[PDB]
Image (cartoon, rainbow over all chains, first blue to last red; front, side, top):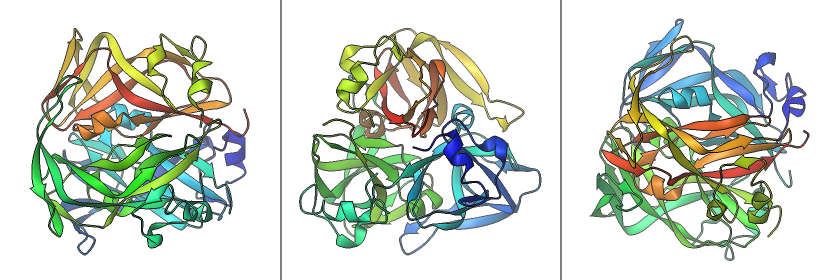
Length: 143
Length: 143
Length: 143
């Protein structure tokens, strides 16, 4: 796992559209952005049928209804080298305040922004541009 | 974490009943199989009382009700060395399509198939034999 | 990640108020304890407004209502070094028995007990002092 300093060298290269203060002791705190966010409104029948999304204008605050999953576009764009992978964990503040999210991975070689799924246990809200996820960088044994 | 190459040499030895296609850039995608799957219908009173399960025939597609947790047996059987461990994360497609799952680990020394717990946020379904989880291989500092 | 023996050497200094039996093959099993636990009753409006908590006496068992998130104080107190971090995952028994928890991390330098959030999918209960989470220790590339 990469330390605060090692992650700092990734800014502008591996992690684009970053925020310096978001580089933590041992990870980077991903933020949610975008002109819009999405609310899943009808279940998926995988793998053939994806869930039905309701598009919502992401103004200053995203309003979430209890028992619904929402998709957010990350502020950050990623350019993963075949040498690194990232474990996406949830920021503790979100976990302790009633938000759910499963663990997922940004695989080596991945390019682009990432869309994260946050499920609201209660009617609640998340501020646009706030940090929601704690990224842990893992190095592959072989590229 | 083991790369695609390292995981490939695990097939037939550490990962049985596998699919060569499921070996990813830095992980193996576990699949759900079995003649049956289970639905939790009554809550647990841990550790003394486990949750009450309803057994359901796993035909070709497993139907899930919103706000219920389901147990699926993996197609893959594991034979973990005292030198390796596995972090079970959720496949992104499942996360983004309204399925929840907590992070868990297959510890060194573990033998057998794994029963994974997927919680449905919406009435939905998952195809029998489809990939649902993204396995990351962790090597112990000492066997 | 750190192995069983490596975790034993952390008892008394990195992991306080521990239980020897809770040291596993490749992790430490955190326990829930404390005079009381908390039920989230009203959603959060992050980051400005945290979720509204209801304080509940934690006697011998913690009774949880379906679709509610609860905060538990860990028995264990941590004193993380500058080159060690912990990935908090859920014990498989809790996952398979209908309890949800998102992945979170105890960062290098962190000092104190941790409050974990468990979301109940069903009306259920958890015994005071029982193991709920499986801690995986990660070493930083640089302190």
